[PDB]
Length: 299
Length: 303
Ligand SMILES: O=C(O)/C=C/c1ccc(O)cc1
Ligand SMILES: O=C(O)/C=C/c1ccc(O)cc1
Ligand SMILES: O=C(O)/C=C/c1ccc(O)cc1
Ligand SMILES: O=C(O)/C=C/c1ccc(O)cc1
Figure 1 (tube, rainbow over the protein chains, first blue to last red):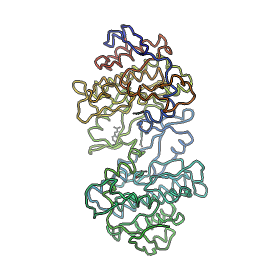
Figure 2 (cartoon, rainbow over the protein chains, first blue to last red; figure 1 turned 90 degrees about the vertical axis):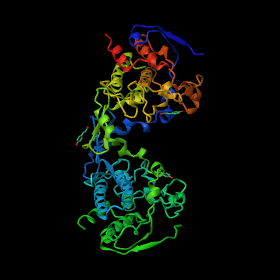
Figure 3 (cartoon, rainbow over the protein chains, first blue to last red; figure 1 turned 30 degrees about the vertical axis):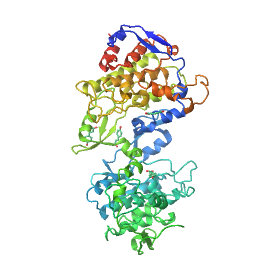
């Protein structure tokens, strides 16, 4: 068996309401090595499933400074809680409302199931552009993951903001993510063509594309490139990976989704027009964050 | 160039699109019915845009009004509480876990490993022990809430042990008038290596003592700087620079979950006497043999 060693019934241990010795097993050398191996930190007690770190993220003081410098009515920034101890510093994303656009999208789907009014779709479009302009022209940073999930709304669209701003996609002088160890990822359904090319060139327009698909969501209340494999005329009121078109999905990844003009009307004119040019197959053909702003400002 | 055939339409050149630096026309495909159903299917919300990977929702969590009341009311020196950002009344409020320092006890038990490798001084372990006990006592007595999963990574340290708080407190494991989690919904999950017998058993009963067990295991972590029941079958090739899944005795693991791990007696000394006693009683197979948080606070504030 394993070497045991009795621990005599002490007075202190009695204070714990347990008066008796306790036998315990022995261990020569603590398997520290295995417990701290990469396998362990990865499989046992995953840091991805850890709450505190998810909120208070350890950041390299240089990035931390950049992330704390984000200051714009349409961007959600970060805040620290101490002066950079030597090396890193914890940062927490600040608050920008109780709901995310995504939350409102599905909130609606379960009620009216009616597209967002054109007036509100444009408003969001304005503020999001405003915020992208700031990120692109001011901070020289590409968001890289635009979508309804990363747009938080305050009340009845009192304020529209963009969150989860990174520091890993620095925009070169030619407004192009030239940095060597910099990879665009975003969220599959929202990826631009150049993010799928496996070799394409990531420009600032990568965001404009995603910005377009986000306006699309407010029109269709749906996810880009997710269509029922076999319609059946929207028959059964239940869906799963069986009636999902694996086919069309990986096919359209990076292309402009089909517009539901049938459900919309005439007021959604500008919305559709803006959506179209932002999803244009070619990067150069897509407006700059800035262009979209003034082109929408008083015009 | 593969594409497909399907209804399309032409958006005439307009002043607007021109103003967007285009001044041309665009041809767009067409859709009659929006896949709104499939998109919000329980399947879609689970595999596409996984909220478990959403940053904003990770910090600002939506809680039911009654749960937020409880969470907002957490107020103890050794408990990391929550903060709201808008006046509630509605049937749902967002709360963010508060700040309690830069490092977790797990971070420390590991900076410690990357150097000294010498088990935290006995005195510090007792300090950590008393503070955790006070916080756990607050949860059990004052709020009637079992923590759920005590472990080093859920203990945050401020500066040089200037502050020690338990975090990630939830409300789904409410305690009985009998100190047992009987709510039909409740379900002890914890973290495998730290699970007590009761939580490993097929349908054991969970009491405030389940926390005492994992609490004990956390003190063990401070002496061994290891994860409970993670041992290599190879005492032989042990000390080999790197370690892999192929050194981990998969059986001994699942066989020891819930049992008191072995104590590295030869690495400690006689100042680790109280620490070793506390560790032992807190890890008895029988919950009734483990002291309550209250009894631990008293025994440590000794005299
Ligand atoms: O709960 C955890 O964090 C870890 C679970 C786990 C389960 C089986 C393993 O072999 C390792 C980790
Ligand atoms: O955005 C704010 O006003 C405050 C945010 C915040 C986030 C985490 C905290 O621990 C405290 C404040
Ligand atoms: O990145 C995501 O959020 C989603 C990824 C994903 C990958 C394969 C699928 O079939 C669906 C979603
Ligand atoms: O409990 C909290 O931490 C926050 C309370 C709160 C109350 C009213 C506000 O307008 C914002 C926060």
